[PDB]
Each structure stands twice: as structure tokens, then as C-alpha cells.
Amino acid sequence: KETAAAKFERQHMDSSTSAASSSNYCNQMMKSRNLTKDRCKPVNTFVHESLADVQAVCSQKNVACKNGQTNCYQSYSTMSITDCRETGSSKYPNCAYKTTQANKHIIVACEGNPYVPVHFDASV
Amino acid sequence: KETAAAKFERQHMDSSTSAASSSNYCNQMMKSRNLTKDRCKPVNTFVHESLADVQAVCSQKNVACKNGQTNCYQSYSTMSITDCRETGSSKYPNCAYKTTQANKHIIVACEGNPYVPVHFDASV
Image 1 (cartoon, each protein chain N blue to C red):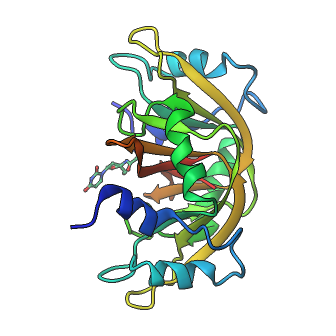
Image 2 (cartoon, rainbow over the protein chains, first blue to last red):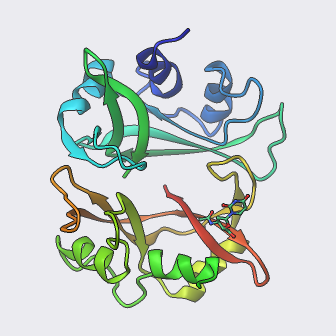
């Protein structure tokens, strides 16, 4: 239904903020992006950069993905990212998360034509 | 026949060094730890802290693991870790790695009695 590119954007992009505002950012974002609909998605990272900057990563440092594929790319520059981790007290449907704000390099998996991110591998 | 805890130790503990020595660290360790044996393991993290300090994370902050279950723990403090990522040029049996040294929080999955790390979930 939803495009892989569109899926990465809904799950990992937040260009409208430069950073996680408060400690409640994850609680709010995990829910508005539908990642809490049938279960509490345990982990998720939001990137606070323009789409253009994120798409540009597909042409930066080529590295192996977690699974062995070689279409992974690491940003040369650090980016404003928000780490969301489900806490030990969260119970669906009251999904609860720990918000962690940081500047880190990102690793995404790119595919298609045009060549854009379709998968969030990791942040380092 | 290694236990899941012994496996964790071989793969992710580097108590003997306070930090990644140099840019060759990953090439050396991936090999000596047998992670380059039949194939190049694409990614891996070494923790540079005493085994005691890492086992202690199993009683620190409880978080959801990547798989959704809640036997993961996030260390209270940052720890010295080295990130090893297989580069695009790497070719078995001559595995090539990019070494990244950083001070980050670690998330491990815990199991057994005593309750010790058996899986490296991520660094944040």
C-alpha cells in the first residue's frame, strides 16, 4: 500500500523540529506516527533533518547493513536524532517510552530509483 | 560448546583496553575473536569495561529489547565502546572494518542465574 520511501518518512522523519522538545516527545511521536497501533513498537529513531539531507546519505559512506547487505550508508556528519526505547513499565495500549536526544551519524539502507533511504539501520 | 554468556564475552568484551587502539583495531579484534571465520560478520561492538561492570547492567534500567520483550537493560552511565562496521570494500577472507570509538549507554539482553548479559541490543 504505502511506498518503502513513504514508510521510512512516516516512521523516521521529523523535519518540523530541530530536536526532541520535552521528555514526552517519544510518547507523543510513537503514537502520532501510528507505531503504537496494535502493539508497542519497542524501539524507534526519529531524525530531525530535512528530507534532502537524509536522502543525501544514500551517496555518503558505504558500509555493510546489520543483515549483511551492502546497500547501507553512514552520514559523514552527525545529525540531530531522537532515540525512543520502550520502558519496562509500558503495557499496551499505554505504550511508554524513554526519550533520548543526541547528535549521531545515521546508517540507512537505500533502494530504488531514485535511490533513497527505505530502512533505518542504526545510529553511531 | 559455549554458553550464551561466554559467547557474549568473546564477541563484545574488551576489558584489556580502555579504548579502540587505532583504525586497525576492528580488523585485528574481529579476527582474533573468530568473527571472520567463515564469513565477515558485518557489525559488532566491543565494550571496554570490566566484566563486573557490564554484568551489573542487568540490574540497571529495564527497557524493551528490539524484539519487544522486557529482559533488556540500559546502563545508567556511558561506557567506552568501539563500533566495528564492515566496509564496502571488504572481501572474505580479508574482512575490512571501520573502527569508531565512543562513550555511550549500552543496552543488553539478560538471562539466567546469575542474571547476566547474553545479547548486545544496542548502544545509545
